[PDB]
Length: 48
Length: 49
Picture 1 (spheres, rainbow over the protein chains, first blue to last red):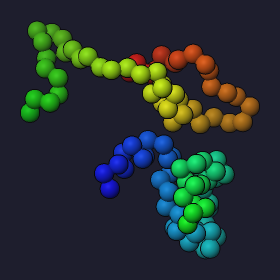
Picture 2 (cartoon, rainbow over the protein chains, first blue to last red; picture 1 turned 180 degrees about the vertical axis):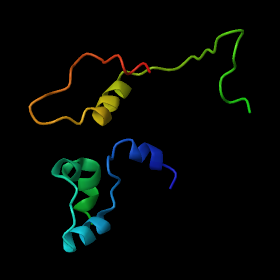
Picture 3 (cartoon, rainbow over the protein chains, first blue to last red; picture 1 turned 120 degrees about the vertical axis):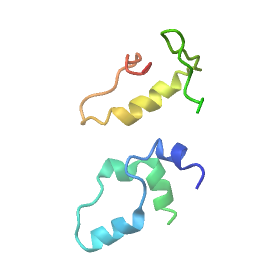
Picture 4 (tube, chains in turn cyan, red; picture 1 turned 135 degrees about the horizontal axis):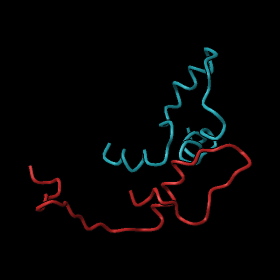
């Protein structure tokens, strides 16, 4: 909760992965490859 | 109440700490261009703003 501002300096979309999973399951548009392969969303995504 | 800086006779003044790496993570947010280009090495004038 407290460090959301300094966290959101970096991330362009905001890292909601499970709704992206719902989108890919229901065949919705997906976030692009750069916004997926950036580190702040990749290194938690592979851990999850 | 008194956290915005005070207004003088005509002016409003501030003293701020400037770091050059904040220009780098400024350009990382702004410049989201295509493939073939690349950002510059010198600093851009829209960083003092």
